Length: 100
Image 1 (tube, rainbow, N blue to C red):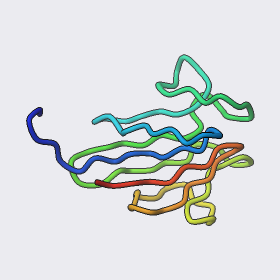
Image 2 (image 1 turned 180 degrees about the vertical axis):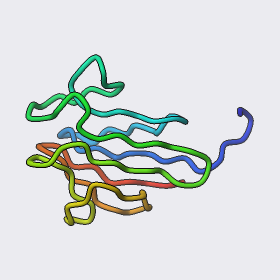
Image 3 (image 1 turned 45 degrees about the horizontal axis):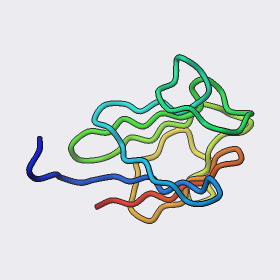
Image 4 (image 1 turned 30 degrees about the vertical axis):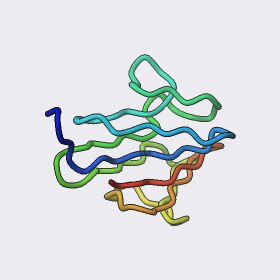
């Protein structure tokens, strides 16, 4: 709703400068494809390389790749739930999660 917002999960992405993308409510699919909602600039990224289901409590982080898969806090996982200040690193793009 508008007026007031709840937990705002902002993905701070090092594109080179440092951009921010806030999670939409629902699942945000990151990768290179038309099958992806958010498209990454570099390559090696699958169509669905990673997806985040954001709901009004926690952000479900799912890594959808094995070889160039994403690490959370530098640890390789398939499934993780986002936390403020966690370090998410994926092929040629690393991102810090900020939860407001």
